[PDB]
Length: 58
Image (cartoon, rainbow, N blue to C red; front, side, top):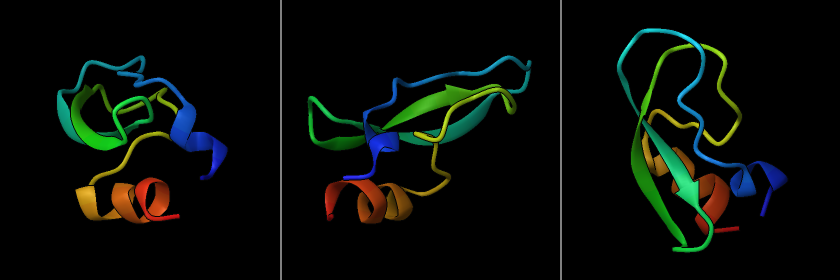
């Protein structure tokens, strides 16, 4: 798996309230989180499809 898949969920440094998906390595699932729109990390996907393609099905 890419190393970004092991990064923690990170809501970022902004004040927006946006739906994103993160890979939860311990659960082997792409899960929902709230993102503030800036200052996150790479474990941050708009679609479940992209998180699964990148992190689950490697």
